[PDB]
Image (cartoon, rainbow over all chains, first blue to last red; front, side, top):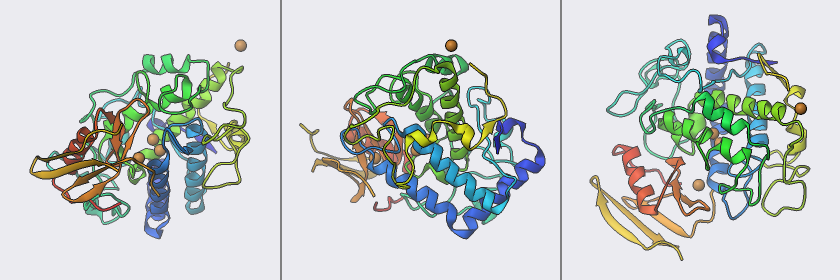
Length: 276
Length: 78
Ligand SMILES: [Cu+2]
Ligand SMILES: [Cu+2]
Ligand SMILES: [Cu+2]
Ligand SMILES: [Cu+2]
């Protein structure tokens, strides 16, 4: 499996990715990914148990969650892989990402409703079922709540941080994981959720298929960081309360550890990933 | 200590806060009487389930951001 930059997909690849996502939605499988993510977002806390977010396991947890979703896509069409969105480069609403043949564009100004693309409510094919309010249509406000996506220079600043994570292993930490996640510093991952707006800014953010492409690029940046820092590795490495240590297993799967997920090449490669 | 309670009408909706699948929380927020999941970050800022990647300084700020997000929509209980 090769994960490709969304900007490089062929028309056929776009078509098959959209169709596989819509079939997972139709069959009911998609919404359970939305529900899993919301459960963890609502339960991960800085002072208590934390696994999917605001903690060192944010990266391996989303790596495995994306692998579950990619496998489900492949169960519909084995040719499909998750593409990634390099938001440092494709930073405008005119990126082909947001074209009607791929994810559709921003929401109208009255109610944020996405009006085109395969996931527009008018298609009948994308009900928002796992939700925190009455609205049942996909919403976005690209660039509405924050003006700008992170820039390449900002990303480079984060990639240069040598320590994977640091005590207290939460949203106050210094180190790579939290700067990539975005609770400290120039803010990479959190700010992208805010920039898309709509459901992507909420605990039910996998309602928007861009979630997957965002996290596939966050996941690529982890791989890039590993190449810049071959001498740095996941921490903590044992006995830390409330935090997933290197060789501890992770919920919900219970059968996989951060250690099993550090090397993406066991599962997939990227179209391009610079060497050390 | 937890933040002080609050009660006001913001953009036509009643928002309330009070010290007290989802977490602990020693603080509760409501929008027209429907509980809004909110969480406190280590640095003292707050988020809610409808703005969960966007820290704001206080629970009232999180309630107000939820009203702005909702654009009149009823909240669903969590
Ligand atoms: Cu929360
Ligand atoms: Cu997440
Ligand atoms: Cu995310
Ligand atoms: Cu070297």
